Image (cartoon, rainbow, N blue to C red; front, side):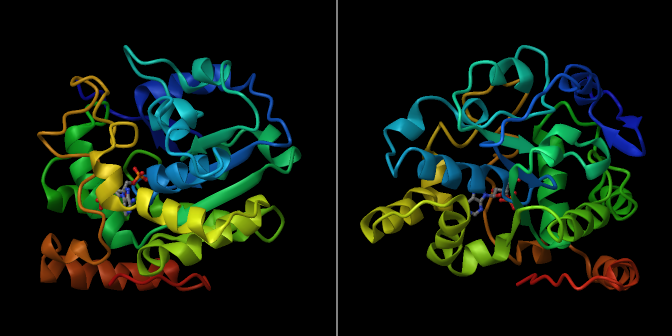
Length: 287
Ligand SMILES: Nc1ncnc2c1ncn2[C@@H]1O[C@H](COP(=O)(O)O)[C@@H](OP(=O)(O)O)[C@H]1O
């Protein structure tokens, strides 16, 4: 009934995900695993659908075997009336696609020791906050988000599920200096998908014919992923997710934040961004 978050080692989490960390202690990573890591609302499902297509040889028929949350186990995931990411993992064939949003501080050390390849996607903070706000509304395990203005404040101080966005994109950016990480930008996936898909291939190590590349580019577009029940979380139960309130597959654009951000909010957020982001070579596009 909109349980409030629970804090674990500085990080605020969904009551249940906090509990899901118990059995996560048991998790043994294989070396052929690949970790998809992102701050919520930055392209998890998109890069997931890309990566599984790669893993099925460009075969849309196989990418339909189950919905995306069953093909790519959500490591820390746990909710009522759905199986825990870890329960789902016990039936996932290798080589396995795995999904988290946990900060390094909560990440299972087995993934780091096993040098598991990581595909990380970042997205400009403004679009993330907007996206995250509507998601909080329709994804009923989160706390009451309140007014946009109040939610935006919380977001600036990382008083939201998975903590601070600013900490998250920065720490994983530094991690890639010691660990195998392809660091991708949502807005780059918008500008030229084909380009970002060939980078994933290089990284994962697969060659595929253009026929099959161009193919994937089309079957991973917002529009196709929106109508595909295996990728749009519409098969989930209503009490866990409610698409009338807001669809998971909401808009899929860069620069949309502008229709929610007040000009006073923008001015303030900008000044706060510069202050937090200033010792960091990362750099985002918002349009
Ligand atoms: N194929 C695609 N291309 C572009 N954006 C996509 C996409 N599939 C999903 N999205 C968008 O990516 C966000 C989902 O993030 P995550 O998977 O990390 O939860 C949502 O953003 P919006 O709410 O801004 O539309 C969703 O609509």
